[PDB]
Image 1 (cartoon, rainbow over the protein chains, first blue to last red):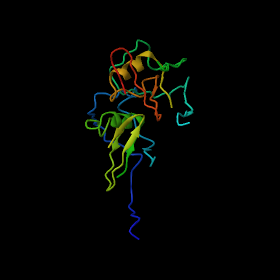
Image 2: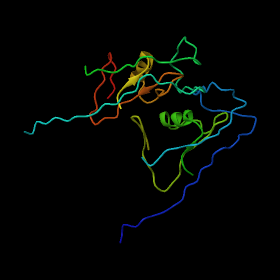
Image 3: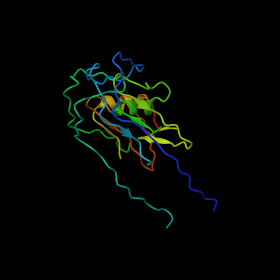
Image 4: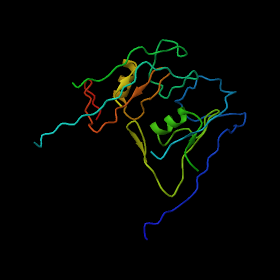
Amino acid sequence: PLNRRMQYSYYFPVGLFMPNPKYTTSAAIKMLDNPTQQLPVEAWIVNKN
Amino acid sequence: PLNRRMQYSYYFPVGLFMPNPKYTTSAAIKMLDNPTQQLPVEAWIVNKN
Amino acid sequence: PALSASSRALIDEFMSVKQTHAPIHYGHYIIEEVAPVRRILKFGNKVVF
Amino acid sequence: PALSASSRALIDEFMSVKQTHAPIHYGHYIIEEVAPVRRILKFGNKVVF
């Protein structure tokens, strides 16, 4: 009886839009898109495995 | 009889194409070819030695 | 909150450098998870705890 | 999976910097072997376990 099963929720959004005066803080990534117009359409989640 | 052998299956891609909105993560690598149109026709492996 | 990134660029920049990955990019964002359990993330060979 | 590198440049930069190497370049990609045998790569002086 001491192998209890503990349950809790998770939540995460997809499809958000950042305000227009945009900023960064990572010197690495160069996405080759137009910076001012890009918008996220999908989400990526890391599975249990 | 204890000197045994194990058999694996080694998996290997070659000749793939990436989606169009192409991105990079590291700034060090520099190539004089245009980034929009690049396609690999070979695959490089490390040998046993 | 659970691990949600808008593109593979942000998940790769999170996985390669843990501390100074950009939490938010121009139009793409990422969230690190905060959960009572902590899980080892493995990608290729690199490991983030 | 086994070590696959589309260009000599990507495998060079992998050998040089183990953690911060870029897994997906603009059109070229690299795959790190995840196999129960962990071999030692001795390209030149530098070594990756």
